Image (cartoon, grey):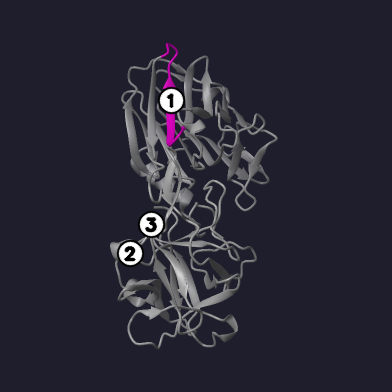
Amino acid sequence: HMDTSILNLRYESNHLIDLSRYASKINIGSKVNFDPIDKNQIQLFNLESSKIEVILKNAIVYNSMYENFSTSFWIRIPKYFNSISLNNEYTIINCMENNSGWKVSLNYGEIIWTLQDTQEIKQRVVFKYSQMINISDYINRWIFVTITNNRLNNSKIYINGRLIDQKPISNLGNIHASNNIMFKLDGCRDTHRYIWIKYFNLFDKELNEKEIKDLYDNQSNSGILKDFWGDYLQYDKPYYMLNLYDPNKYVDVNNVGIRGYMYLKGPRGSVMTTNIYLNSSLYRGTKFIIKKYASGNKDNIVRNNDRVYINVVVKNKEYRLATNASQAGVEKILSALEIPDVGNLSQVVVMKSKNDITNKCKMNLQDNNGNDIGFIGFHQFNNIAKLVASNWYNRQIERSSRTLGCSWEFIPVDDGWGERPLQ
């Protein structure tokens, strides 16, 4: 089966359009920005002209006492930086008319759904996320939102397919929403605030948990690897590294060449504004750059199963991540080699999405005959956490504790994070 999406806003054939059978009219303001690589990603600034208006067909305007309905979308919310954002709820998706209808709003550390009937009875469901946390799944990262409404019982908000908050709405009577949906920051006091949004949908039922998991999967299922923030992973782009097993450590190098080694050291140290955020520093350690090797695709997007080289940046010069797999022991210690001098050492890496926190990548080192040397992780020798390739990883159960050591994320500098690199 059944068509249940009654609005399916997607970028297709050079335009953001409703792909549903209703073909609701879309009006885009002059100051809306679209990601050049993924045009379904839409940026709305705190400006009057940064807006999108959807004009609903009369048949799907919500005017009911009993009809169930849901909405889903992805969002990326920059870190809150300033105390002007405390206690400042601001609408972002508005379908209220004459004090009845629905809206999505944000506040410091919050995503809020509000329903209101025609006699002023209201309910809210709220997702709260902390900004006092070493590494956040949510701050400035793409997250999947699903809100469902059953008129006989509850409204529910899900994040990344997981139920977060449910509240009763059965006391609400006739809810008569607006004929339009306005995507716009409304009432936000932070002049530099923006959001990214993608894949907005409305459904004429309460989605079940399976439907929501499938939507999450399907709209995240891609043959494209992602960076830490959830954007497409790219070749020729410097990234800071995060190991998910040792999230408070960063990658560094003890001398270049075959007698040196890559290793993890910590702690990261902190970035802070008092009363506003306290997180781990993300822009630490040697940057990695992913280089094309086998891919025939002429764009610079890294796809699942691409065979690549990894370069390490040391003093503004690129070296090649490599090992001599002939060394004793299953764990092959990785070094940063002069590119001209790698010779027949093992350097080819298969990039894999772990297929699971969002945005996890695995890197399987292979020799020059294509034989696996093993996923890249680390091993204690015995007081230094050196990076290694090890087939021990490849033999372990997927997504288990033992594969965290070989799961990585790639962090590019992003204005929604606000940290200033040390150098």
Say which amino acid is labelled 1.
Thr
Tell me whether circle 2 and circle 1 mark residues in contact (CB < 8 Å): no
| Residue receiving disc 3 | 356
First reached walking from the N terminus: tag 3 or tag 1: 1
Residue nearest the viewer, comparing 2 with 278: 278
Which quarter of the rendered picture does the C terminus lie within?
Answer: bottom right
Q: Position of residue 222 (x, y in %)?
A: 49, 56
First reached walking from the N terminus: tag 2 or tag 1: 1
Residue nearest the viewer, comparing 322 with 79: 79
Q: Residue at horizontal 56%, vertical 35%? A: 21
Q: Residue at horizontal 68%, vertical 45%? A: 14
Q: Residue at horizontal 58%, vertical 39%? A: 19
* Residue neighbourhood size for the residue with mark 1, other residues' Cα within 10 Å, grouped as few (<14), some (14–19), many (≥20): some
- Secondary element at image label 3: loop
Residue nearest the viewer, comparing 305 with 254: 254
| Residue receiving disc 1 | 114
| Residue receiving disc 2 | 398
For this orientation, the residue located farthest to the top is 119
- Secondary element at image label 2: loop
Residue 206 in view in this figure: no
